Each structure stands twice: as structure tokens, then as C-alpha cells.
Image (tube, each protein chain N blue to C red):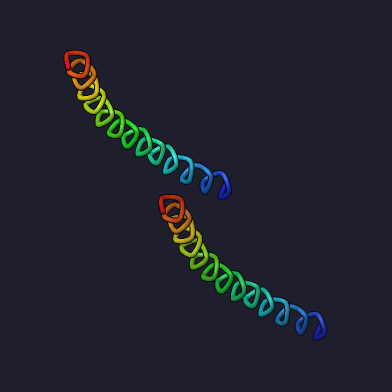
Length: 49
Length: 49
């Protein structure tokens, strides 16, 4: 029973870690979207030039 | 999708570039037409001379 308890607590905190990862990843994704949009507009300008 | 978006923006801008080309060609042609009229008149006078 005590071993079961140990594993349960560890697994729960690990799930929280996974959520930490999803958070950081999504922030990076958000920033990269704007990078992409700017690059698209830059290609448009280069076309005009 | 992103590559399609890039293509679409570029092609739109390029269409407008082609419009610029049409415009400049027309300006040049109009000037040439006035020149042609003058030359016609000069040939007439040459005959008279």
C-alpha cells in the first residue's frame, strides 16, 4: 500500500510537469505565429520591390 | 496552408505589378502617336516643297 501511495503522488506531480511543458510550448507557438505573419508580409514587399 | 498563403500574397502583388507595366506602355504609345502626327505633317510639307 505504501508503494502504491508513492507512485500515485509521483504520477500526479508528473502530470503537472506535462502541463508545464504544454504551457511553455504554447507560448513559443504563439510567438512563432507572429514571426510567420511578419515573414509573409516581408515576402509580399520583396515581390513589390 | 502557409505556403499557399505566401503564394497568394505574392501573386496578388505581381498582378498589380503587371498593371503598372500596362500603364507605362500606354503612356509611351500616346507620346509616339503625337510624334507620328507631326511626321505625317512634315511629309505633306516636303511634298509641297
